[PDB]
Image (cartoon, grey):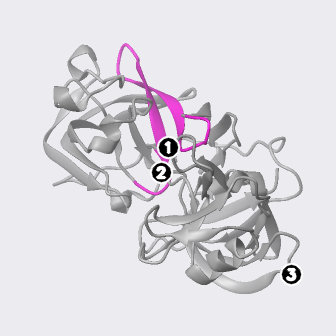
Amino acid sequence: STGSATTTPIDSLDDAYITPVQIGTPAQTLNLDFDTGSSDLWVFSSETTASEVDGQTIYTPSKSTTAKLLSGATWSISYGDGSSSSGDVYTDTVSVGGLTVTGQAVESAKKVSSSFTEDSTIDGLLGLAFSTLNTVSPTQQKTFFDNAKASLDSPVFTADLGYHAPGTYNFGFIDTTAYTGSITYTAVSTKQGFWEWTSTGYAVGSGTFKSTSIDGIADTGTTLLYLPATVVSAYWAQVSGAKSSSSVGGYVFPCSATLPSFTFGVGSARIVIPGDYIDFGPISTGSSSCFGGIQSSAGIGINIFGDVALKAAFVVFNGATTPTLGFASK
């Protein structure tokens, strides 16, 4: 089997992408944030504290004839950005772009962090990291991809995120028309539960490539590119007027400035992030100071290849027995 669904940015800055997901019988369609940095499928629901719902579409298990309470099961998660949520668990039918999993754990939110309430366009998350990170207790649950894997024509999914435009998630096949050149594959460590790999280095604009190992995660659920402070400093040094602002919480720059591209290495191959992708606009409405899309990972504890980097490539998440990652230009 295969599936294919369009993913759409939630706003003009590509802060995140939402993908429609059918849950239950009859189908309830929710717009979920596909997150390769986590492993819970959780949704706003009829069970969510009313004061914590503000515009989101909810899942109502009682209206689904295929929903079954997973008795005794609870879940609770906190994300790298200080967000969180918690609740109970049903199993139900979940379909993504034509691909159907029966018995998928659907985690029903009883409580969500303010940040989720405040984002009316995201109805929940669909985690695509490794199932070892799943928070359901006492019995850990599998991700949508893990459940679908054996049925898929090939045990892969691909992320093809757009710049200021929609993109595509595919399951079970590689669309050879979606990228240029070849796909370079690189090794993955699952030891932290992430799609963790090692970039071979970077260049800033037309600068010479610096060969150096950068360990990080491919995370569709994170907006920006977070890299070591040395790297980030080398980038912003090439932008006139840029500075790191503690009050703002990162590098900012005047929008009159031209942003250089940023190249990262995948084995011997090279992915170029155009400068325009690194502009995240005014820090506040009307400000002349713009927020940068490349920021320091210092004190995150891990480097994150977020949407800023991934949207510059066609990315293969290969769930073969030994997982790997593939990157192609497009």
- Going by the numbered disc 2, the residue's amino acid type is Leu
36 sits to left or right of 208: left
Contact flag, marks 2 and 1 (Cβ < 8 Å): yes
Give the quarter of the figure containing the N terminus: top right
Answer whether residue 187 is visible to the viewer in this image: yes
Report which residue position mark 2 lands on. Answer: 128
Q: Position of residue 61 (x, y in %)?
A: 24, 23
Label 3 element class: loop
Query: Closer to the N terminus: mark 1 or mark 3?
Result: 1
223 sits to left or right of 41: right
The front one of 71 and 248 is 248
For discs 1 and 3, the disc positioned in front in the rendered view: 3
Magenta highlight range = 11-38
Query: Closer to the N terminus: mark 2 or mark 3?
Result: 2
- Going by the numbered disc 1, the residue's amino acid type is Phe
Where, by quadrant of the figure, is residue 260 drawn?
bottom right
Label 2 element class: loop
The front one of 210 and 321 is 210
Label 1 element class: strand
Report which residue position mark 1 lands on. Answer: 34
Q: Name the residue located 42 percent from the left edge and 66 percent from the top edge.
A: 193
Report which residue position mark 3 lands on. Answer: 208
Q: Name the residue located 53 percent from the left edge and 33 percent from the top edge.
A: 19
For discs 2 and 1, the disc positioned in front in the rendered view: 1
Neighbourhood count class around disc 1 (C-alpha, 10 Å): few under 14, some 14–19, many 20 upward: many
Q: In whole angstroms, how far apart are the C-alphas of marks 2 and 3?
A: 35 Å
- Going by the numbered disc 3, the residue's amino acid type is Thr
Q: Position of residue 12 (x, y in %)?
A: 62, 36
